[PDB]
Image (cartoon, rainbow, N blue to C red):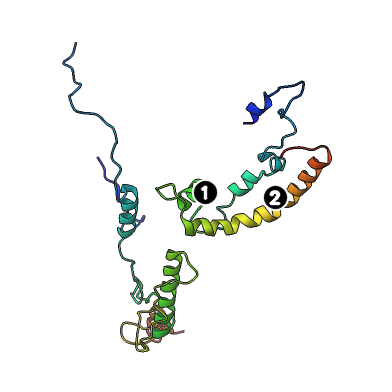
Amino acid sequence: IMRVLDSISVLGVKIMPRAHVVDSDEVGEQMEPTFEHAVMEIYKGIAGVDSLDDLTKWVLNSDLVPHDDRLGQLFQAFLPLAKDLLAPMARQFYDNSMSEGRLLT
Amino acid sequence: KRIPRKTKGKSSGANPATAEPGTSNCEHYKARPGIASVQKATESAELPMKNNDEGTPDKRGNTKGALVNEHVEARDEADDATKKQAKDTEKAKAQVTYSDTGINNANELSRSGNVDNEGGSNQKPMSTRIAEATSAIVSKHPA
């Protein structure tokens, strides 16, 4: 959709180029451990799992439908990272982006 | 040709067409119960019973286990089973419990390492218990 919206022009203007737009991963990409890498290292501290693949097997059944109890348990470890490791950097980045122009995020 | 051994003590003591009418590998049918789910459940139920190896002697002769009273062992062991069931259920409290039972069961005894086979208590291990008894008879050469 970004690629399609980039190549849109009617008058002598560009509606939404490959600019003025902040990608969803772009909020957390610029960290020494990325948020994706940070949540990859979550099997530590969880009993019965020793690797990311083991965690995926343990949290997802054969149906590929989430197991409610296991995923609810895993959210209790996911949330503190998203509330302490992401939120301040996200706030700073959003404020900086808003300062230097009006952008769609 | 040699089968390995699992538990050893290391101490050692222009061709006819072969396409056949009717053979095609395709999967159009999904198992209603679910092959993977039933296989996983069968694997879980497949495990053999735990080796309750309490009070059993050793090669030396000492009884194995923890020096605790029989009824205390039974109570703590039922509590451990309840906790294990809670973990298996993945809830704070298991619905099925072995400790909240209304039935009085104060006479329950569970096997522990407190009592020897003869009926005594392993306050001192059987090896030493024989050791002092045997060493009470000594005789050295005269000076």
B17 with respect to B56 (left or right): left
Q: Is residue B53 above or below residue B70?
A: above
Q: Is residue B72 above or below residue A42?
A: below
Quarter occupied by residue B24 = top left
For residue A13, the mark is none
Q: Distance from label 2 to label 1 (Cα)?
A: 23 Å
Q: Nearer the viewer, residue B40 or A76?
A: A76
Q: Nearer the viewer, residue A39 or B138?
A: A39
Q: How many marks?
A: 2
Point 47% across, 72% down: residue: B93
Q: Are marks 2 and 1 in contact (CB under 8 Å)?
A: no
Residue projecting furthest to the left: B16
Q: Is residue B140 above or below residue A98?
A: below
Q: Residues within 10 Å of mark 2 (few under 14, many from 20)?
A: some
The percent position of residue A100, horizontal first and vertical second, equals: 83, 38
Quarter occupied by residue A7 = top right
Q: Which residue is mark 1?
A: A51
Q: Which residue is mark 2?
A: A86
Element at label 1: loop
Residue type, label 1: Ser
- Whether residue B138 appears in this view of the structure is no
- Check if mark 2 and mark 1 are on a common chain: yes
The chain letter under disc 1 is A
The chain letter under disc 2 is A
The percent position of residue A55, horizontal first and vertical second, equals: 50, 50
Quarter occupied by residue B46 = bottom left
Point 46% across, 55% down: residue: A67
- Whether residue B75 appears in this view of the structure is yes
Q: Residues within 10 Å of mark 1 (few under 14, many from 20)?
A: some
